[PDB]
Structures are given as C-alpha cells and as structure tokens.
Image (cartoon, rainbow over all chains, first blue to last red; front, side):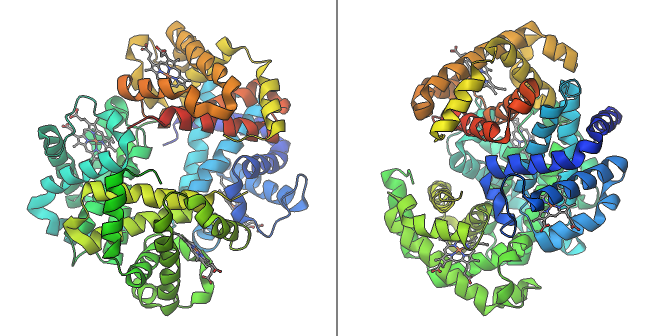
Length: 141
Length: 141
Length: 146
Length: 146
Ligand code: HEM
Ligand code: HEM
Ligand code: HEM
Ligand code: HEM
C-alpha cells in the first residue's frame, strides 16, 4: 500500500518529468524491448526500430495513463478501470511483463532525475509502478 | 478477487482435505524443498529429511493457517494479520517463494483429491493460494 | 535437462503409463481455464467461454495432442532439448508470437495433471524430476527468441 | 551470458569510469531501502532504521565494496561466469543461506544506480548489455545451490 510519503514522492518525481513524460514512455519501451526481447511478442504489428512512429505514440499513451494514475493515486482501480478491462479482456499481456516494463520506467526515470532519484524516491516509485501493475492485472481472472 | 464460486469451490475441497490438512501441509513442503532447492535457504535450522519432526510440525502450522484463511475467506487480511506481520517484519521470505509453495500445495491437493480437483476447482484453488500469498506479502514495503 | 540417472528412469517409467492425447487435451484445457489470458492465441478454436466449453472443445483437445505429442517426442532427447525444439522455438517466436511464459504456465498445469492422474505414484522426488523436465522444455522453446 | 563483441566493449568502457567502492555501497544501500526484507541478513550492521541510516551505515558501505569488488573481478571472465563464481555460489548457499532471488534484486538496483550516476550515457543498448551481465552473475551465483 502506497504510504502518504510514497504519494508525495511519486507526485514530486513525476511532476519533474513534466512535459518529457511521453518521450520517457517511448524510451522506457525501447529499453524494455532491447533488454527483454520476449516483450516484443505483444507488438508484432509494431515497427520496433529506434524512433518508430508506433513506439513514439505508444510511449505517450503509457506516460499519460501513468500521469492519470498519479492524479488519482488514492483510487487507481476506478481511474484505470477502462485500462484494466483492456489488458485483462483483450490485450491479455501475461502479468510477468508488467514487472519488466516497470523496471525500465524506473531505469528511465533514474537516467533523467539525477537529483530527484534518491533512495526513498526510488523505493516509492518502484512501489507505485508495482501497484499500477497490480491494478492493470486485477481483472485477469 | 475470489468470486462466490471460488469461495464455494475452495471450502468444498479444503473441507475434503479435512483431518489430512496437517499431513498435506508437510507433503507440500517436501515437494517444494525438492523441486525448488532455493526455498531451503529459509530453513537451515530444520532437519529437512523425509518424515522430519520439524517438517511435520511446520506443515501442520501452515495447514492450520490455511484452514483459518478458508474459514475466513471474506476477510483474510484480518484473519492473517499476525501472520502477515510475522513474514514482513521477521521471516522476510522473499515474495517469489510464495508462488513456489502455492504451486506445491496445488500439486499436493491434485494428488489427493481425484474427484474434487476439476479444472474449475483447480482454478479457484490457484486464485485462493495467490490471495493468501498476496495477504502474507502485503506489509513488506 | 540435468536429471540424475534415477530421475531419468522415474521420468521414462511414469511417462510410459501416460496417454498423451488424453493428457494433452486435459493440460491445454486446464491452461485456458486456470490462466484465461492464454486464450488470446486460440480465437479460431471457437467456444472457450466456460470451463465446460473449453474442456469439451475439439480444437483444444486436438492442439493438446499436438503440443504434448511434441513434448513426448522431446523426452527421448533430454540430452539436447535445445537442438530438439530449436525449429519450434523459432516458430513460436517469429510466426506464432507466443510469450515464453506460456510454456512455463503449461508446465505448471502438466505437473498438476500428472499429480491428478497418478495420485501418490507421483511422489515428491518424481515431481522434482518432472520440474527439471518442464523447466528444460520451456527453456529450450524460449532459447530462440530474439 | 553471451554478450556481443560490441556489448562486451560497452560494459568494459562504462565500468572503467565506475568507482567500485562507491557504487558498491550505493547499490547495496538501495537494496536494503527499496526491498527492506533483504535486511534479514544484516542485523549485525546496526542502524538500518531509515534510508539515511542505511545509506550512511559504514557496515553497509564496507559490505557493498566487498560485494561489488567481487562482481567487478567477474567482469574479466564474462565468458565463464559460472566457473569464476562457483566457489562464491557454494558459500552463499551452504554457509550464508542466501536466497538467489537477492542477487537478481541487487542486479535491478545496480542497473538503476548506473542509470542514475551516468544518465544519458547509460543508453538502452548499454543497459541491455548490463542486463545480460547482472542476469549472468545472478545465474552463476545461484548455479551451485542445492
Ligand atoms: C505500467 C504499465 C502499463 C501501462 C500504464 C499501460 C498503458 C497502456 C495504454 C494507455 C494503452 C493504450 C490503450 C488505448 O489505446 O485505449 C495500452 C496498450 C497496449 N499495452 Fe499496455 N500498459 C502497461 C503495460 C503493458 C505491458 C507490460 C505490456 C506488454 C509488454 C503492454 C502491452 C500493450 C499493448 C500490446 C498495447 C496495444 C498497443 C497498440 O497496438 O497500440 N502494456 N497500454
Ligand atoms: C504460502 C503460505 C504460507 C503460509 C500460510 C505460511 C504460514 C506460516 C505459519 C503458520 C508459520 C508458523 C507461525 C507460528 O508458529 O507462529 C510460518 C513460519 C515460517 N514460514 Fe511461512 N507461510 C507461508 C509461506 C512461507 C514460504 C513461501 C516460506 C519460505 C519458502 C515460509 C517460511 C517460513 C519460515 C522460515 C517460518 C519459520 C520456520 C520455523 O522456524 O519454524 N513461509 N509460516
Ligand atoms: C511443451 C510446450 C509446447 C510445445 C512442445 C508446443 C508444440 C507445438 C507444435 C508441435 C506446434 C505445431 C507446429 C507446426 O507443425 O506447425 C505448435 C503450434 C502452436 N502452439 Fe505450441 N507448443 C507448446 C506450448 C504452447 C503454448 C503454452 C502456447 C500458447 C498458449 C502455444 C501456442 C501455439 C499455437 C498458437 C500454435 C499454432 C497452431 C494452431 O494452434 O493453429 N504452444 N505448438
Ligand atoms: C552480485 C552478487 C554478489 C556478490 C558478487 C557477492 C559477493 C560476496 C563476497 C565476496 C562476500 C564475502 C565472502 C568471503 O569471501 O568470505 C559476500 C558475503 C556476504 N554476502 Fe554476498 N554477494 C553478492 C550479493 C549478495 C546479496 C544480494 C546478499 C543478500 C542481500 C548477500 C549477502 C551476503 C552476506 C550475508 C554475506 C556475509 C557478510 C558477513 O560477514 O556478515 N550477498 N558476498
């Protein structure tokens, strides 16, 4: 469960991201596809090359949905309802890949927040992404 | 989320385990220790040989907690409160290990419940063990 | 996989008593019921809305026979599952686009099915032996992903 | 594991700028902070109550430099991580009783620490190279478990 400090830490870090969020989403995706190729099984319809229009666009979507979660950190299940429905009923991405993408979002943030990414913020951000993962997979069965 | 059907399936099958709960807990432990040697790192003070007094003892404890969880499927976090405390603040068993024991508890049940272990009951039991694990890991961070 | 001599015997001994067609359908069916998301790959199969629909579905039963058939065939080559499933691995990646976790999920199910079918004959040491086998088959099938 | 000739150079290059002592204490420190359960092995280390306490703990720093110094040495044996870490594997399993999952977790932290300290330089391809390294080191340290 995300503590008050966690929510304070998350909002602060993601706020710093600011207008770079979409760019970071694409970077997180690229890092994941490269470090964990199995995740590419879910994007056989995507041009997955560096700088592709599809990865750029999807990176923006993922970032915005995370901005949405940050904005409704006290009620993510309801805020991401349509997305958990999507992943569980249509996309059907196996739950294990969420930890993979979370790892690369976390790495992308570390790469861009030299001052912000402290041990405590590291911990809160990891908890946060795990929870977002938990809700997006909460209706799988 | 354990649906009403899940709770019915679980209570029926656990109800069938009944007086054998202790023996089954000890067998699942052994199945785990053998199939996944890494789990033994948490029991260096245990004689882990087949028929061990410690394994039998701990197996009965594990089974009893499960009996309690089943009798309180509607409020597990409360029923397993001191238990999630114990694992989070003392034992500190890495979360990945809970899926290994769940797998072996499922296997043990499958081997003992010929009539009961239908695909549906199998599905409900898997969900239930994951729930117990989620609860037991709820206070780690 | 890296089984000991006895483990290699226990595997073969037990497996001889296995009805691959019956167990393949059972295992594939239980995969779809227990981990519903796996259904994503079998839209062409038709009705998969309920456990009974899934378990009684002819296509699930057919694919089960094929999959466990290849799994069976692989048991005669525990010395090199890599080379044995190399072609299949390339096929599941490049053509079928199957996430290798699916192979591990199927393994969990198979072990449960063997447990259910054999009762106490599926002792803890026999399971450990089969754990290395399903782990090795999954690993061999995942080996060619890129 | 098997890095490409270029990946091996990317690793080697990046590591030439890594102060092993500092990154060691930092990495181990964050491990105890981000996954507090890992603290189960270090009760003797004293004050581990808050992040500032863990990170500032002299025992944590000293153990971190030991752990990362060994990891560092192993980078000179990229093509045989299993063999170079065999002794350490037996020690962590037989004496220390450390769950191998801990190695995977420290690997996650190390990558985050490198990304953090190096920034844009720690590119997606450089990360991929280090992912192979931390995974190989974890598998090598877990190999002799039984
Ligand atoms: C923090 C976790 C994640 C977030 C917030 C997220 C968010 C989203 C969003 C916003 C969409 C677009 C929905 C729409 O267009 O209506 C989506 C689509 C998608 N996601 Fe997820 N997702 C997450 C994790 C994953 C993971 C782990 C995978 C698999 C590696 C995945 C695979 C997909 C796929 C295949 C699509 C469809 C892409 C397309 O065809 O455009 N997602 N996700
Ligand atoms: C998934 C279900 C689990 C349940 C319901 C469970 C239940 C219990 C119970 C009832 C106790 C005894 C508490 C007491 O006597 O006050 C206990 C202790 C313990 N558990 Fe868990 N546990 C679970 C998972 C795990 C796992 C996955 C491991 C590690 C592989 C583990 C390792 C231990 C250890 C180290 C002890 C203490 C052993 C001893 O010193 O006697 N537990 N657990
Ligand atoms: C022990 C594991 C497995 C083995 C050895 C295996 C084997 C096979 C074989 C022999 C084929 C036919 C190739 C051909 O001749 O064209 C095949 C196709 C296929 N497999 Fe696998 N498979 C395994 C697990 C699975 C799993 C768990 C999934 C996903 C849930 C999967 C999805 C598919 C799909 C979608 C096809 C395409 C053919 C069709 O069903 O129309 N397989 N598999
Ligand atoms: C990259 C992986 C790691 C490497 C290469 C590594 C290396 C080492 C080395 C060289 C020692 C000293 C052993 C000796 O030669 O006497 C050691 C000790 C130890 N390691 Fe590891 N280690 C690793 C990760 C970990 C992790 C993640 C944990 C657990 C969170 C851990 C827990 C311990 C403990 C408990 C000791 C004993 C410290 C004491 O004296 O109290 N190690 N490790």
